[PDB]
Image: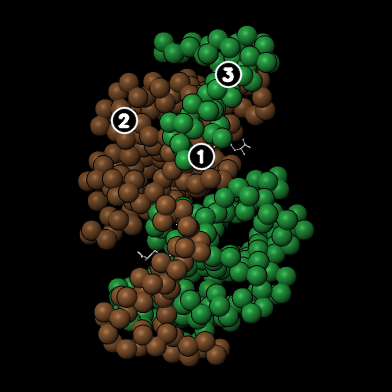
Chain colours: A brown, B green
Amino acid sequence: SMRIDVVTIFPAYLDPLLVDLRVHDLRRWTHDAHRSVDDAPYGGGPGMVMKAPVWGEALDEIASAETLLVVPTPAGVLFDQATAARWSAERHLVFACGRYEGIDQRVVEDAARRMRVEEVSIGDYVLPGGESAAVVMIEAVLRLLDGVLGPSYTRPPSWRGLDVPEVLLSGDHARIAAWRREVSLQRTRERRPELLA
Amino acid sequence: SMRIDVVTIFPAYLDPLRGLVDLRVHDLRRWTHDAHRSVDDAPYGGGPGMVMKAPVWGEALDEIASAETLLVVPTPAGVLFDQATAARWSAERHLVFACGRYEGIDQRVVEDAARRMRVEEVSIGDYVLPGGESAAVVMIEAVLRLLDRLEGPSYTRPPSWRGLDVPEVLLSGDHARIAAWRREVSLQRTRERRPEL
Ligand SMILES: Nc1ncnc2c1ncn2[C@@H]1O[C@H](CSCC[C@H](N)C(=O)O)[C@@H](O)[C@H]1O
Ligand SMILES: Nc1ncnc2c1ncn2[C@@H]1O[C@H](CSCC[C@H](N)C(=O)O)[C@@H](O)[C@H]1O
């Protein structure tokens, strides 16, 4: 039903992880003895940029017109639960994992001529590579596929002088739902006030 | 200089991530006391899934953490992790990541730990992961990267590729025009993808 390809210069990074998950070494698409995937940026600046000649060949082999190409980037639109649910209905996801200063922008523009491309950030922080971001996104999608085939407490009722809220022991499904909504609302006001506009 | 302990029921998860930094991974089952080495139990108040037990977690953190520790608890209900947090955590002597699984850790673990250490409940973004291990990887990567509004596009050779040319300004050699162009693309990119910034 779903195929997921991950392209990276660090295939061992996805070892931690109906669904056919494949991980590809980007160096398989290099033609030199040094298996070179990067080169100096135009306009100067530190670091190296991943070459379009290498990425172009990798995507020519792996992706088709039906593919949804995900490019992790700290400059992309934010990944969220609505995106994970939408991507869980896809037949083919491809994750182009960037390293160094990222992939040559023309790779994305060229892919977008035949397939759908989404440049996505997992959050407002900087990772050294796109591998952990692909892992995070694949986990959120796979979690939804597994499911479609507030604070938590368990025993003991009292621990280190801290008791489970009495409402959770009441057996009253309505009062429990009302309490969980109140704690959720209080947490949102304190931690994420922007979610209440 | 910095010690990082990761506590999880999946120690092999952090294998690809591993002298200034001492990174250690602990199997949470080391602090269980039953024959089944069980870390979870049914939730109070009903609901699907299991909850990780406070006795196991309390004992693990009593051994691993001290008053100088900063305990990070991944949770989709936490304050958002960001670059400012990664920079702040890079100055810490001891970070401990309590990786949740199932429906999460019994809330009393955090309240009890906060009696003898600093605790931060942190979300890596507005999506749901099956466990906190990938979230710990993402956070540790952002901190380790530092110890080692939107970004513009990057380009490398060739100057023309599949009919797509590198912007002429990047070939001009004019540091002033290049800086002006990068500021403009950064601004346009932010307007299209993150207008709230
Ligand atoms: N917040 C984020 N979300 C998604 N991918 C990100 C990301 N931050 C970084 N990446 C990934 O990491 C790659 C390199 S970004 C630059 C990191 C490098 N240490 C440096 O100092 O330049 C990007 O191409 C992207 O794939
Ligand atoms: N956005 C996020 N940021 C940080 N940690 C998260 C997270 N989403 C999930 N987690 C981690 O994943 C654990 C389980 S929460 C969700 C999994 C649960 N089996 C379910 O299907 O509801 C949490 O305790 C936390 O450690």
- Sequence order check: which comes first, mark 1 or mark 3? 3
The yes-or-no answer for disc 1 within 8 Å of ligand 1 is no
SS assignment at label 1: loop
Q: How many marks?
A: 3
**Residue A33: image x %, image y %?**
57, 23
Asked if labels 3 and 1 touch by Cβ distance under 8 angstroms, the answer is: no
Residue behind mark 1: B197
Q: How dense is the environment of label 1, judged by Cα within 10 Å: few (below 14), some, or many (20 and up)?
A: few
Q: Residues within 10 Å of mark 2 (few under 14, many from 20)?
A: some
Q: CA distance from mark 1 to mark 2?
A: 26 Å
Q: Nearer the viewer, mark 1 or mark 2?
A: 1
In this view, the mark in front (3 or 2): 3
Q: Where ligand 2 lies, by quadrant?
A: bottom left
Residue identified by numbered label 3: B181
Residue, x 42% and y 80% (percent of image)? A153
Q: Which residue is mark 2?
A: A116
Looking at this view, name the residue that lies furthest to the front.
A197
Q: Quadrant of the N terminus of chain B?
A: bottom right
* Kind of residue sitting beneath label 3: Trp
Residue B23 locus on image (x, y percent) = 65, 60
The image position of residue A8, as x and y in percent, is 48, 37
Can the viewer see residue B119?
Answer: yes
Image quadrant of residue B27? bottom right
Residue at image x 30%, y 27%?
A: A115
Q: Chain of mark 1?
A: B
Q: Note whether A6 is above or below B63 in the view shown.
A: above
Label 1 and label 3 in one chain? yes
What kind of element bears circle 3?
helix
Q: Is residue B10 left or right of residue A173?
A: right
Q: Amino acid at mark 2?
A: Arg
Please identify the quarter of the rendering in which residue B118 is found. bottom right
